[PDB]
Each structure stands twice: as C-alpha cells, then as structure tokens.
Image: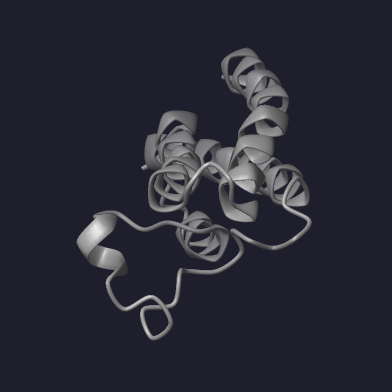
Length: 121
C-alpha cells in the first residue's frame, strides 16, 4: 500500500536522524571504550554480572537494519552502555569515569534529538 510506503519513508528518515545522533554520541567516547562488545574471552564472567550487554557496534547493526522504531528504543540501548559500565566497574576506574562523561555529554545531543523527532514527526 501507499500507507506502508509512507510509514517506511518515516522509518528511513528516523534511521537517518538516529545515525547522526549515534555519530555525535560516539564522538563523546574518544578512547573507544564503548565501541565494541566486552570480550567474553577476556572477561569470562561478564554475563554473570551484566544481563543485557550493549556497545556502539551492536547499536549500529540494529540501526542499519532499521531496528529502532522510535527514539525511546535507541535511548534504551545507549543507557545500557552507560549503566552496564557503571555497575561492572568501580568508581575509581577509567571505565566508570568514561561512562559518566559520555552520559553527561550525550544528554545535550539527546535533548535536541527528542525535539527534532517530535518537531519533524
């Protein structure tokens, strides 16, 4: 149908906007601490601690399959990256500290993304 096409164009455009959001958030991780999944070869107990691992490469795979229906779903995955890290790592670690800085700097990006998503519909 024509409606299904219009819906698909909307999703494509959301995907475009989320891709720019993802790029802007990933720039706030210049150390690349959150770029890839925590390695289960190197951290073999990880899934005993963290039940829903997340990282920017995994988000990008989902994004490119158009698997984010709305900004909430995308934000859920970003918050998992941060929250997983702040539980597994202690406060005095470069990893925890990187997550705090990513959360703080990402807030600004996500605030305007939400306005754009609502504004453009």
